[PDB]
Structures are given as C-alpha cells and as structure tokens.
Amino acid sequence: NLFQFAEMIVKMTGKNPLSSYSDYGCYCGWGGKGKPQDATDRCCFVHDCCYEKVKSCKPKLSLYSYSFQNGGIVCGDNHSCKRAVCECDRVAATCFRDNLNTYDKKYHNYPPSQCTGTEQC
Image (cartoon, rainbow, N blue to C red; front, side, top):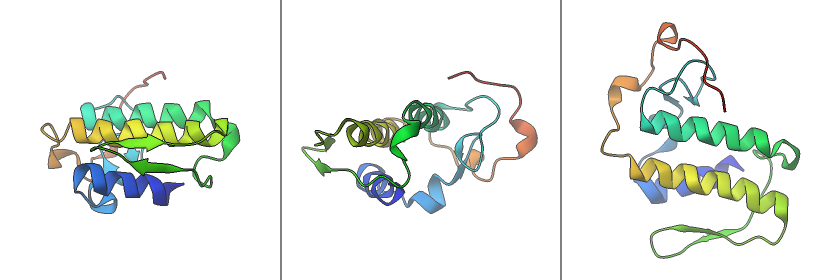
C-alpha cells in the first residue's frame, strides 16, 4: 500500500514523500500527462506503468511483505500479486535514490502547461 511505499522512500532517500514526491514533474503524484522531465520523474512514470500491469491486486490497498536488507529492499512474498506490487515500489524507491544528484526543485509544483504530449508505457 502507499504507507509502505512511503516507508521505502524515507529509508532510501531521506526525504519526506509529501514534500518531495507528491508534486514533481509530470508524473510524480498529481500528473499523468506529458513526457518525463528528468530521471526522478521517469522513476514515477515507470512506477505508474508497473501499477497498471498489476491492476488486479489493488496496488494502493494491498498490504505486502518486505524487509530492509543491506541498504536495499527485499520483497519477501510467495503470493504473486503482492510480490509484484512490492516490486514496483521497491524499484521506484531505489530509482529515486539513484537519481538524487539530478533532483531539482525546479520541478516542484510544476506548471501543467509544461506537460505536453504523450509517453507510452
């Protein structure tokens, strides 16, 4: 669920998800239109595509199983639907950590007029 996605974001980036990843670019949080502005925005986009591929597990409401191991996340489910939701969140959160060097506050509360075009999953 997103309480768990938020748990993974604070441990991997040191950032608060509401201040940093709820409105950034064209896809983090309130978006869903345009092209990924940078790498962080791309982590969000891949994460939205990942969720649509697992439409049937109720991604946001699904409580899954994981642990933090050695500066990383390990999804520990047997159950296919929950392991997949966990994996979407796992790679998006580590994707955010990988790209903290390019993280630019320019993209906070990004103007809607700037999200132009379509990007295909």
